[PDB]
Image (cartoon, grey):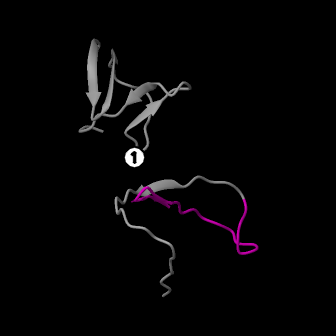
Amino acid sequence: KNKCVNFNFNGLTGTGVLTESNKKFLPFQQFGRDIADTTDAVRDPQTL
Amino acid sequence: KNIDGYFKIYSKHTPINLVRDLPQGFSALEPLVDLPIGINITRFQTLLA
């Protein structure tokens, strides 16, 4: 956290700054996207 | 719904005050379970109690 990293969240590849989110994801949701279909927030593959 | 073999199913359960056997309004059905079956379906039938 708090660092630029090359992440791979079980296929959701990319590069960015990972940090704890204030939003709420659905019970069956893996990730979410913004208006431009860009990965804005994700859930850990192992942790909820 | 069979989605390329994924027999995805949604669901929702809410209260009602029945008027005409189909109360009107609005809601949203959430995904219940993913089912990677991979089999073709063309008909169905209900199981009544």
SS label for mark 1? loop
**Dominant secondary-structure state across the stretch colored magenta:** loop
Vertical arrangement, residue B14 with respect to residue A39, above or below = below
The percent position of residue A33, horizontal first and vertical second, equals 47, 30
Q: Could you tell me which residue is drawn at 51 percent across and 26 percent down?
A: A34
Chain identifier of the residue bearing label 1 in the image? A
Q: Could you tell me which residue is drawn at 45 percent across and 30 percent down?
A: A23
| Count of marks placed on residues | 1
Q: In the image as oriented, which residue stretches furthest toward the left?
A: A46
B44 inside magenta stretch? no
Vertical arrangement, residue B36 with respect to residue A8, above or below = below
Residue A40, quarter of picture: top left
Using the image as rendered, state which of residue B44 and residue B10 is in the foreground.
B44
Query: Mark 1 highlights which residue?
Result: A27
Residue A1 appears in view:
no
Other-residue count near label 1 (Cα within 10 Å), few / some / many at <14 / 14–19 / ≥20: few
B21 inside magenta stretch? yes
Q: Amino acid at mark 1?
A: Pro
Q: Which residues are magenta?
A: B1-24
The percent position of residue A7, horizontal first and vertical second, equals 27, 23
The percent position of residue B34, horizontal first and vertical second, equals 38, 56
Using the image as rendered, state which of residue B34 and residue A1 is in the foreground.
B34
B3 sits left or right of A43 in the view: right
Q: In the image as oriented, which residue stretches furthest toward the right?
A: B20
Q: In the image as oriented, which residue stretches furthest toward the bottom?
A: B49
Residue B24 appears in view:
yes
Residue A41, quarter of picture: top left
The percent position of residue A10, horizontal first and vertical second, equals 27, 35
A20 sits left or right of B12 in the view: left
